[PDB]
Amino acid sequence: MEDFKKIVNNIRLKDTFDFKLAAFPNQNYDQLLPSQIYKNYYQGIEIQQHKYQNELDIKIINFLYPDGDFGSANKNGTLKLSLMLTDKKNNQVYYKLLEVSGFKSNPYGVDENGTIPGLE
């Protein structure tokens, strides 16, 4: 169908697949702060794999702040997606961290509950 090692280097959000969180079914990426996603994906992630579904399986197993703390992520509207990629031919599982931006952001990194990065 297509060699896996050629399609894995092409996995990109909004292209190959999209995700929707069980906690925010009707909200786009740009209306969600990275911190909101990080604190609510435990409710469930629905993957919409648009391409390569014959050859590959894409799962987001963890959402991580690029630098380890929400303020930094909320400022850049960025997240580090920890992925699990299954090669459907051989059935081997591969892991890959992918950094994506385009999520809601605010200049100081304050979160959805008013918390300020580093204060208190």
Image: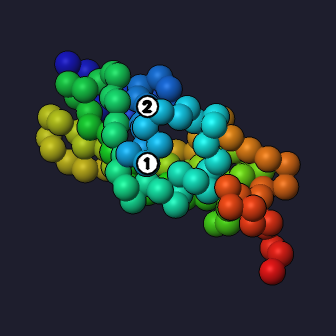
Q: Which mark is residue 73?
A: none
Q: Secondary structure at mark 2?
A: strand
- Give the residue drawn at x 64%, y 48%: 33
Q: Which residue is mark 1?
A: 23
**What residue is at 52 percent from the left and 61 percent from the top?**
39
Identified by mark 1, the residue type is Ala
Residue toward you, 55 or 78: 78
Vertical arrangement, residue 85 with respect to residue 56, above or below: below
Q: Mark 2 — residue?
A: 18
Q: Residue 100 appears at what percent x and percent y? A: 59, 40
Label 1: how many residues lie within 10 Å, few (<14), some (14-19) or many (20+)? Answer: some
x, y percentage for residue 18? 43, 31
Query: Where residue 5 sits: x, y (%)?
Result: 34, 34
> Is 37 drawn above or below residue 12 in the view shown?
below
Dot placed on the residue nearer the N-terminal end, 1 or 2: 2
The answer to whether residue 55 shows anywhere in this view is yes
Please tell me whether mark 1 sits on a helix, a strand or a loop: loop
Asked if residue 63 lies left or right of residue 54, the reply is right
Q: Quadrant of residue 58?
A: top left
Residue at (58, 53) in percent of width and height:
36
Q: Is residue 35 rendered to the left or right of residue 48?
A: right
Name the mark nearer the viewer: 1 or 2: 1
The residue positioned 64% from the left and 66% from the top of the image is 68
Mark 2: amino acid: Asp
Between 120 and 67, the one nearer to me in the picture: 120
What is the quadrant of the N terminus in the image? Answer: top left
* Real-space CA distance between mark 1 and mark 2, rounded to the nearest whole angstrom: 15 Å
